[PDB]
Length: 264
Ligand SMILES: *C/C=C(C)/C=C/C=C(C)/C=C/C1=C(C)CCCC1(C)C
Ligand SMILES: CCCCCCCC/C=C\CCCCCCCC(=O)O
Ligand SMILES: [Cl-]
Ligand SMILES: [Cl-]
Image (cartoon, rainbow, N blue to C red; front, side, top):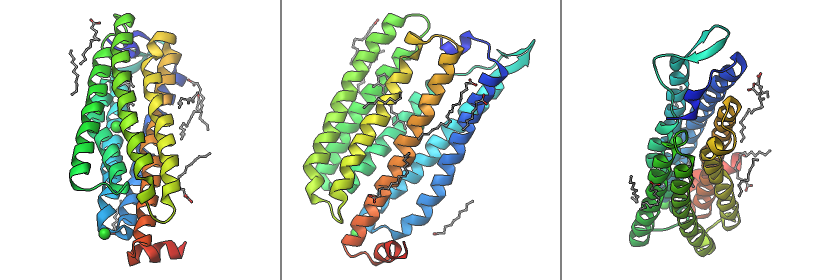
């Protein structure tokens, strides 16, 4: 049902996609160790924001690892090209993983925004419901990326509605709570919003690839877009969230944070 299944791949195409996914695994697990070691310099009220980046690194790292092994399982070099064998490859498992990773990305944002108690629980709930609506409708949509492009588009429109409403909740909370933020991170959090808008918008662009580039090079482009988007939305984002957490920790008088920033 996926466009990947439609084509044979050149050695170049096949190896590049393998390299993209493998590099993706390496970057996320390398970043994992960074987040782990810097977590000790985060104050208790923010430390979970850094822990969530560790959780996202392993979650994303495992889905990329799984996609890479699925890629090599599904194809073999036969008569001059990589051709589909008995096992299958699908991006559908990415969508399932988003059900977990996207709530984690959203939660760590709410934490460094200094949301607490009732407002934190209510905002998280609405955000996660919006994200789940987006992911599920998008998942259904991509089941038709070969059979029914028109249906892919309509589910995509519904998904985009959830996306836009989710982004409005995010923007509203960021620009409202910006003032509460310490150590100059009221400025930094604004860049985080725009990083999110940019990186997350790459995913619906990837979703539309079967509509505007239905060929083997389109398959490569989609994996390339996922790689840019994953690294930006999880790793670069996590680094900024953790930077914000440490800076606010230091401004709040957390000595390990103050000492850590002092060494650099
Ligand atoms: C780390 C993974 C992330 C941040 C995934 C984000 C995914 C999206 C923003 C998905 C968006 C979609 C649409 C807005 C419409 C087309 C269907 C989706 C689910 C790809
Ligand atoms: C934050 C951005 C992260 C960037 C990750 C992507 C790094 C590698 C990017 C690709 C370089 C272009 C490779 C040339 C493609 C050759 C076409 C092909 O062989 O199929
Ligand atoms: Cl604290
Ligand atoms: Cl993920």
